[PDB]
Length: 188
Image (cartoon, rainbow, N blue to C red; front, side):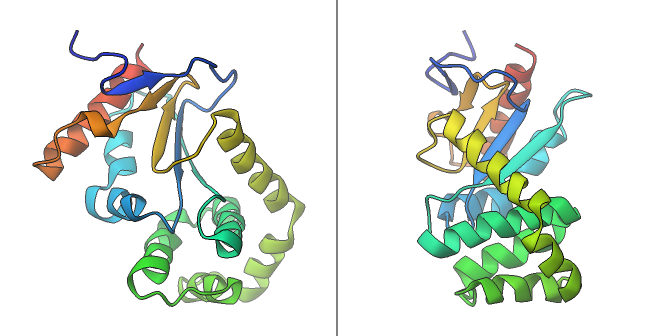
């Protein structure tokens, strides 16, 4: 066929029940994740092609960057709780990978302050049980699918995107193939 298990996607031999429809995993330490977000704009182009009624979820992972990696998962939980993903994603990637000015939890915090979230509000969120369970969710979703690498995308808790099986000569064409595959899997 045109879409083949083992070529643009793989099937999970152990499917995850009740999983989010479209589930993306990343790390602010992850070089391809930086590309996916800032250069390719994957999450965005996927969204623009998903059918109506399909929600998109994106989670941070702990297994890169040791202690700071975990802080970043907690900070991403804060971002999700406050609804400010679209304001901190770029400065966090650049702070970790471009300028390398993020070296501690306090530097992560500075990014939110500079994006205009109030200190009082950030610290309250950071320390909240709602953020605690949002961290738990991120961890559980990664745990449910054996996650050892990022970027990664899962559809319907049963299919996993396989970008290695796609032409990268042209970045625009790569992205559309990626997005179209997600749509196909979505409709499966």
